[PDB]
Image (tube, grey):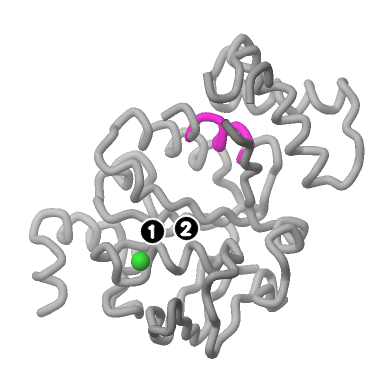
Amino acid sequence: SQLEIRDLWASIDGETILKGVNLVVPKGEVHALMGPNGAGKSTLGKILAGDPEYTVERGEILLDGENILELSPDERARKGLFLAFQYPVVPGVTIANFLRLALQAKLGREVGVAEFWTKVKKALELLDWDESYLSRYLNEGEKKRNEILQLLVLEPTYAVLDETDSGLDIDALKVVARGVNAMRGPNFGALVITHYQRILNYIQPDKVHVMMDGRVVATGGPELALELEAKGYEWLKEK
Ligand SMILES: [Cl-]
């Protein structure tokens, strides 16, 4: 019934970056994780993904009751954690073909044209996007659109979306919001990681967690993100 990070301690290149992270996202809710850059929010996202460069010293990550820290990235996706499929530079690959490859990898079986197009059509309807988009080639903002189509088609139970790399690029933030809002429901939970409050005007969070010095130092409703945007992180560090 929830995605939970419990007493998580982690380090990289021999240095402790996460210092006892406790963060729970109930299935059915969309939460935000904010914080100064380098204070741990993005490192948490990489550890959730299963980035092997990190060493977990203590803690657990439970997805609906099961500890996934020992699972490979592929195994976590099999348990319902969103893992976008990555592709290189390569010419002549339509978004449609790529999505079919991504869905077949996630499902562990072939997916026929009927199942594929029925699912794609539903996703396009929810996103209010034209089917012609699927004819675009990979590598022809844009990377975000492709990931959002995967979000709707792969139907993960939980998704951790780090949008720090979008900054204040409104188009990119809105594409992700369209996808997250389209997935909202009793069977989906999400954690949106961001430095700026901007995206939260498009994706209203049920709860906001703020991370400083490797741990969550404050939580609240959307108003907390608003006050942080108005006053700055230094204000919160003090009180
Ligand atoms: Cl970080």
| Residue at which label 2 appears | 191
Of label 2 and label 1, which has the lower sequence position?
A: 1
Q: Is residue 57 left or right of residue 222?
A: right
Query: Image quadrant for the N terminus?
Result: bottom right
Q: Is residue 150 magenta?
A: yes
At x 77%, y 38%, the residue is 103
Q: Splitting the image into 4 quarters, where does residue 152 fall?
A: top right
The one nearer the camera, 17 or 175, is 17
Q: Main secondary structure of the magenta part?
A: helix
Which residue is depicted at the point 59% across and 14% down? 136
Q: What is the quadrant of residue 230 in the picture?
A: bottom left
* Image location (x, y in percent) of residue 37: 27, 62
Q: Would residue 187 appear left or right of 210 to someone viewing this image?
A: right
Q: Amino acid at mark 1?
A: Ala
Mark 2: few/some/many CA within 10 Å (<14, 14-19, 20+): many
Residue in view at x 70 percent, y 29 percent:
98
Q: What's the magenta region?
A: 144-151
Q: Which mark is residue 80?
A: none
Residue located farthest toward the bottom when viewing the structure as drawn: 58
Residue 8: x and y in percent read 49, 83
What's the residue at 71%, 30% (across, down)? 99
Q: Are marks 2 and 1 in contact (CB under 8 Å)?
A: yes
Pointer 1 residue Cβ closer than 8 Å to ligand 1: no
Quarter of the rendering occupied by the C terminus: bottom left
Graded by Cα atoms within 10 Å as few (under 14), some (14 to 19) or many (20 or more), the crowding at tag 1 reads many
What residue does disc 1 label?
32
- Marks 2/1: CA distance? 5 Å
